[PDB]
Length: 464
Image 1 (spheres, one colour):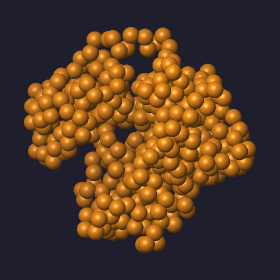
Image 2 (cartoon, one colour):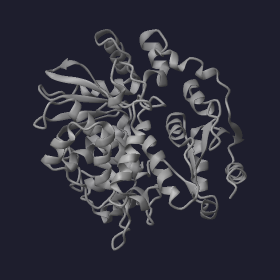
Image 3 (cartoon, rainbow, N blue to C red):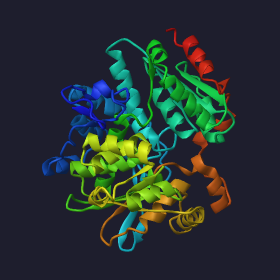
Image 4 (cartoon, rainbow, N blue to C red):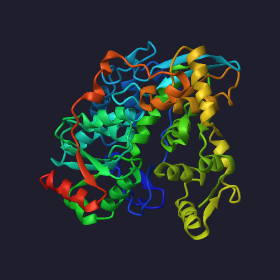
């Protein structure tokens, strides 16, 4: 049973499928399960040797009792294949889906990269998005209807969304991107798509103008009903579930037996990965530390260091757990933010739950990340990107002799080429598979920063 971070859902029934499409709860909160499903010692032992798709089935099954088991297995097996997750760049077996690449021992701990970025758009959101494509298609087939997804992107999330949803029955994607303001690789991956259910709208503004238009359409309830408007952003619970799976996969790959403990480092203070790692640990996965790298973001640093915020969907899910899963406390925190200019979890006695849950944090600077990229290229003979470098720098501050440390690789170097050029004096390396991408014919519709222009476009391209 799924309930709201702000109190709705008690005395009701919301299944996984009921909330799949990712709406907020009725009270403005986010949906969460009423308990975290527990993995027994026997289950954990049985799961160690499962291929990724079957491990995914096991975990998704804990969170979804309303979809027939056979159908969930068919969905995960269709989703997680070597062919889709084909871009393994370090000699790994793509059938692992998220191969673990061990770098070496540091402070007595084996340090590895978990390769989450071998999917079609070379970054970690392909892990959840590919699954959401199949889940959406499956669920929408039951009603013979179409979901018209509206989203915004600066390149990476929209790419992952479009590669997951292209060609899915019952789905269209209307994606707003800032015209001429994205990197060439990301622009080409999106705009080269010819699929008739994918609509790339290049907005004459910046990313925040694109987000503002999605928000404005969010507030037009009659239009949302008329056009069956959907979202695949962080409000989506299924995306978090999907991410729990690779913590299990990485744990097993990093260990020989379930007597061992593993630490993970999450780049970029990303609350979806924070949440997913925390949820895996809460289910019984033997995670020692969850290390959160926050680069030079002072807000994130301040929160993890002190529990305070002075004035993210998934921040709210995390803080709900810090506050004891009491929705009244969450509502108060948001009242403190609005009425009193921030919150202070240390003062209220709730900050102790951050360390309780295994969390620690650290920061990196641009110079630190360049140095880390250069170090890795020389010592371990491989390219890593800026996000992975933020992760590795921070990971290195939290090594315990004897405890594997797994750093999430959240984007491949080709996605963030500027820092690779600065660090390594060259473009990211790329195989023949990607030759000509940026020169392919591009298909997009330019629109101004005008919400009604976007509404008109959607209405003219759905048949509603």
